[PDB]
Amino acid sequence: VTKLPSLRYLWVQGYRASMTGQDLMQMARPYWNIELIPSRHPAHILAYYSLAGQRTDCPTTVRVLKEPI
Amino acid sequence: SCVATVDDVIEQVMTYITDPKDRDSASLVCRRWFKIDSETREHVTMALCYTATPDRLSRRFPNLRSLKLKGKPRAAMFNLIPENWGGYVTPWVTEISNNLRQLKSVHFRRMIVSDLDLDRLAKARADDLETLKLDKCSGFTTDGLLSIVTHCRKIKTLLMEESSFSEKDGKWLHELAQHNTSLEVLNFYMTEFAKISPKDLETIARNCRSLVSVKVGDFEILELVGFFKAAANLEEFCGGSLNEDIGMPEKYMNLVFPRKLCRLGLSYMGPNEMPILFPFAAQIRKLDLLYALLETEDHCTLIQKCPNLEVLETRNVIGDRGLEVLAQYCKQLKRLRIERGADEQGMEDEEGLVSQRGLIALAQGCQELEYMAVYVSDITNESLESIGTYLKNLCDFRLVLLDREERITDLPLDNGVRSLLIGCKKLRRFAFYLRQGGLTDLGLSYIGQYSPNVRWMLLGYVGESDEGLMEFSRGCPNLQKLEMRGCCFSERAIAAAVTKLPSLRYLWVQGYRASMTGQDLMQMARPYWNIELIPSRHPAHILAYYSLAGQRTDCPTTVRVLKEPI
Amino acid sequence: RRASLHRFLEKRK
Amino acid sequence: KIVLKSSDGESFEVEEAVALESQTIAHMVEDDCVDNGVPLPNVTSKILAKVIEYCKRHVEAAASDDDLKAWDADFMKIDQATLFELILAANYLNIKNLLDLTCQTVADMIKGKTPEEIRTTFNIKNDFTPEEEEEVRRENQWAFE
Amino acid sequence: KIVLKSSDGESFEVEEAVALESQTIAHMVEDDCVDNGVPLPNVTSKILAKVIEYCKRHVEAAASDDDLKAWDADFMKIDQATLFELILAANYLNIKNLLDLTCQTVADMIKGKTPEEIRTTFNIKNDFTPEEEEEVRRENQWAFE
Amino acid sequence: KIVLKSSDGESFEVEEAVALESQTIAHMVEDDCVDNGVPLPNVTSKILAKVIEYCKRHVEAAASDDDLKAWDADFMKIDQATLFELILAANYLNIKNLLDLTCQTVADMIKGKTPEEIRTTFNIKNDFTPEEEEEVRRENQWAFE
Ligand SMILES: CC[C@@H]1C[C@@H]2C(=O)CC[C@@H]2[C@@H](C(=O)N[C@@]2(C(=O)O)C[C@@H]2CC)C1
C-alpha cells in the first residue's frame, strides 16, 4: 500500500493475519482510514483516504483500527 | 461540585511542562490543550526562518516571551554560502512590532539584520527588551547598536559575537556606560571594534552590579585593569589582547583578576604570560585556548593545573601529549573541541598532531565527556572502538580527519564507526568527515543502522557508491537534518534517499554527480518541499527543506529555485 | 575553513 | 489552635503553624474571622483532611529532606479525581508547596508520553478534524521548536 | 430538632417543622447532610436569624389570619439593604411565603411612584441618554399600553 | 561534611549547613565539584578560617539575638587589612550576613569625619585640582542634599 503511488481504496479478504493486529499499522498514514470486518467469512480489510476522519456510524461487526490499543 | 476532571486543572498544570517536546505532544491531545499551549508557550526556536511565515508564528504563539531564529545554512560559517543568500530578519521584526507584544528576548543566528530593522525593534520593544543576541549576523552598523542601547534601557544581555557590521563610532558603548545599570552579560567576542573606549567598559563594570560575563575584542589587557577591579561579580571573561614586549619582561604579572573568574580565555596569551592563571587555576571550569599563542608543551603545563576543568576548546597544537595530560588530571571534562590550527608550515610544532594515541588516551581518562569535536591528523579503527566502549553519554561527536598526512594507519573505518555508534547510544549529533578511502558502502550502512537517536549528521567523504547512500537511507529513524559534502552519490540517489528517510526536514549537499538535465533531483518533489540550487559558480549546492510558506520571495540571482518541468 | 579562525590564523602571522 | 470549618459542616482542630501554611488562612487572621472558625466551604471534608495531613508533616521539618520526597511520593499514590481536587484545594487555600507539588505531579504524568498515551491515561476524546491535527503536527515538526 | 450552620460559623437550634418551611433544607434531609448540620454558607447569621423568626411565627398557624398581616407588616419595617438580603435568602432557601410576599413587598414600593420617585427611594442613577429617555417615553405614551 | 580547599593547599573539614551560608559554595553542589572538594583559591587560609568561624556561629541560631550583636562586635575587633580581606571574601563566596558587618564597620569609620579626617585615617592623597574641589563643595552646599 505504501509503495503504490495512486492507491486510494483497498479491500482484501483472506490474508495471513495475526491477533496482534499491529502489522497492518505499518501503513498508518494521515487521512488513511483502515476498517476491519472480523472473521465472523475470513477477516476483511477496508481502507481508503478520507478528508473527513473516521466514520461516526460503524456497526458492532466493524472495528476501526487506530494506533496502539 | 462534580467529579473534578483534568480539564478543571490543565490551564494550571500546562505551565509546569517545560520540555519543548512535551509541549509538542500536549498541544496535540485535543483542541483545548492546543489552545492552552498556544497561549502559554514562552519560548520558540525556528531552525530555519523560511520554514513558516511570521504571521503563522504569531497566530500560533501570540504570547512568546523569547524567540530564536536561524537563517543561513550552517555552511555559511565556512564561506560556502553567498552573502546575499537570505535570512533577512526584517519581516520578523515587523511581526514582532505588531503581534508579539510580550517578547522580552530575541536571538538572531546567521541572519541579515539592518539598521532599520534594529531601530524598529528598539522602538517597538524598548524597555521590555531584556536580551538581544546578534549571533553571527551581518548587515548593520553602530547606528543600529546605538538605537537599541538608547531605547532599551533595561537590557540585561547584549551579544554580537562573530557578527559583521560597519563601525562608524563608539557611542553605543558610551551610551551603555552612561545609563545602563542592568547589564548581566555583554559579548562582542569575535569582533573588530577600533573606536570603543576601554574607559567606557570600565564604567559599565562599576555600574552593573550583576555583570557576570563579558567577552571582548582586541583591547590591551593592561587597559582593562580598572575594569577587572570593578567587575566584582565577573565569572567569565574572554578576549582582550596580551601583547608582550621584550622591554617589560614582567609586563603583566600584576593582574587583579576578579575573584570568581572561572570561565575564561585570554587572546594571544603566550607562555610568558600564561602563569598569571596559576594563582586560581584550581577554580577554572572553562578554558578557551582557541586564540592562544602557546605550544604543545605549554598546554600540558596549564592543563595539568586545572583539575576541575569541564570545558576546553583549543587548536590541535594541544597534541597527543596534551590529550594524555588532560586524560588524567581533568576527570570531570564534559566538553572538548579541538579546532584545526595553522596547517600550512608544519603543524605549529612537531607534536601539534592529535591521533589514535590521544583519542584512546582521552576515551579512558575523561569518561564523563558529553561533547567531543576533533580535527584529527590520523585515526585507527581501534580509537573509535574505545570511544564507544568508555565514554557513554556522549551526545555530540564530531571527527574530521585532516588532509595533511599521506598515509593513514588503517583506513576503511567501518568496524570502528559501528562500535562507536553502538556504545554511545545517547548520541544526538554526529559528524564524520574523512577522505575518499575512508568508509565503504558497508560502513555507511552501519551509520544508518546504529544511530537511532541522531537528529543531525554531517558526513564527510564517506561511501564508495550509490549503494552506500541507499543502504544508509533505510536507517536513521530520527535524522532531521543531513549535511553531506565531498560525496560521489548521484542526483537520483540523493533524491531516492530523501524519499526513504522518515524524519528528514533539511538537506544540504555539496559535490554530487550532477546533470545539466536538472531533472533527476525532481524525483523527490513532494508537496511543501522546497529545493534550492546554488550553481557551480565551488561545486553546485543543493539546499532542501520543508516549509509551510511556499517558495521564498527573496532569492538572490546566484540561487535557482527548482520547480517542475522548465 | 571556519570564519573565526581564518581571521585569527592571519592576525597570528 | 485554630478551627477550620469544611464545606459540609465539619470542624477541624488544627495547630497554629499548620493552618498558616495556607496564605489564604493566614491573610484571614488579620480581619480575624477566626471568631467563628475559618469558614472555607469549597473544600470537601475528605480533601481538607488530606490537606492538613500534608501540612502537618511539612511543618515537622523543624527537626530538619531525604525522607520527605519519600512521604511525598507515597502521599501522591492517590487516584486522579482526588489528585485534581487537591490541586483545586491548594489553589483555593494558598499552599505553594502543595501547588508546585500537585501541578508538578500531574505534569509528570504527561512528560514523555505521546498524544495518544496522554488522552488514554486521562480519558480525553481527540476532537481534532484531521486537517487541524495535520497542520499542528506540521507546525510542530517542520517549523516551531 | 435540626442544626443550621450560618455563613460565619454559627450553629442554630431550630425545630423540625420550622426548618422544613425551606424546601432547600427539606430536599436536604433525603441525602441527609444533617449528620453535620445543614451547611448553608450564603446566609449571613443576622439574616438567617430573621428568616427563622419568620418561619417560627407562620408555622404557629397550627392554632389557626387577621393577626398575621399585622405581624408580617411589622416584620417588614426594616431597611432596604436588609429587605433585599431577605429576598436573596428566601430564594436561596425556598420559602415561597417569604417570595410571593417579599417580592410583592418590594413591588408595593414601586407601585404608584413616578420614575424619579422610584430611583429616589432606591438610590439609582438615571443612566439614559436624553434620546433614549425620550424614545421610551414616546413609545410608552403614544404607542404601547 | 564538605571540603573547602584554600588558596595555599589547605583542606578544611566543614559541616553541611555551614558551608551553605555561602551561595557561591551552594550553587556549586549542583554541578557538584565537591568530588575533589570545592576549589576556592582566592581566599587566604587565615581568612577562610575566620569566615568559617563566623558561619559556624550564625548557623547556631538554631537554638534561637542579643548575644549575637555581642559576638559580632567582638569578631570585628580586627585590623583594617583583615577587615578588608573579609569583605573581599564575603563577596567572593556569597555571604550576605558577613558583609553587612564588615562593610558597616568600615562605614562607621567614615561616619562623622570630615574629608580631611577621612583621608588621614586611611592614608589617601587628595588628588582634586582646586577647581574640582570647589565645584564639588559648591554643589554639595548650595544645590544638592
Ligand atoms: C557544509 C560543511 C562544512 C565544511 C567544513 C569542512 O571543510 C570540514 C568541517 C567544516 C564543517 C564543520 O562543521 N566542522 C566541525 C565543526 O563543528 O566545525 C564539525 C567539525 C568539528 C570537529 C562544515
Image (spheres, coloured by chain):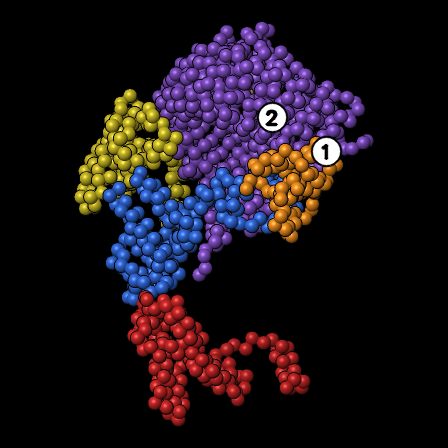
Chain colours: A orange, B purple, C brown, D blue, E red, F yellow
Residue D59 against residue B366 in the figure, above or below:
below
Q: Is mark 2 within 8 Å of ligand 1?
A: no
Q: Is residue F35 left or right of residue B552?
A: left
Residue B89: tell me if it is visible.
no
Q: Position of residue A51 (x, y in %)?
A: 69, 46
Give residue E130's quadrant in the image.
Answer: bottom right
The quadrant of the rendering that contains the N terminus of chain E is bottom left
**Number of residues whose C-alpha sits closer than 10 Å to that of mark 2, classed few (under 14), some (14–19) or many (20 or more):** many
Give the residue pinned by disc 2. Answer: B475
Q: Which quadrant does the C terminus of chain E fall into? A: bottom right
Q: Is residue E45 above or below residue B178?
A: below
Q: Position of residue E27 (x, y in %)?
A: 41, 72
Q: Which chain does the residue under circle 1 lie in?
A: A
Which label is found at residue A4? 1
| Residue B189 relative to residue E81: left or right | right
Question: Is disc 2 placed on a helix, strand or loop?
Answer: loop
Residue F44 sits above or below residue E54 on the image = above
Query: Is E70 or B156 nearer to us in this picture?
Result: E70
Name the residue at 48% across, 18% down: B387
Q: Nearer the viewer, residue D44 or B191?
A: D44
Asked if A36 appears above or below B86 in the picture, the reply is below
Give percent across and percent down for residue B270.
46, 15
Q: Secondary structure at mark 1?
A: loop
Residue at 42%, 78% (x, y): give it: E95
